[PDB]
Every structure is written in C-alpha cells, then in structure tokens.
Image (cartoon, rainbow, N blue to C red; front, side):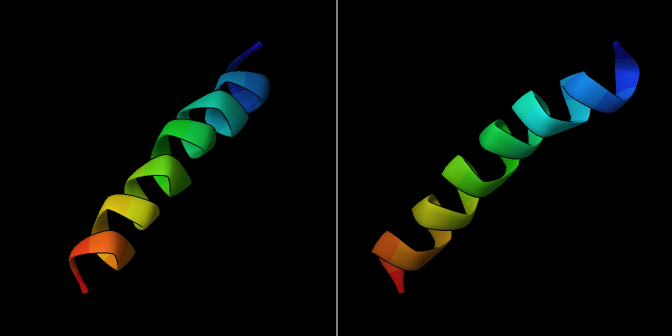
Length: 24
C-alpha cells in the first residue's frame, strides 16, 4: 500500500500545503 500511503502522506502533504497557505 505504498501508492496509497502516498495519498495519506499526500493528505499529510497537502495538509501541509495548507500550513503554507495559512501563513501566506
């Protein structure tokens, strides 16, 4: 479930993208 995890990690990835936005 590596490609899947990438989605979660992506969830973690974007959730982060938000941390970037919030600050922006």
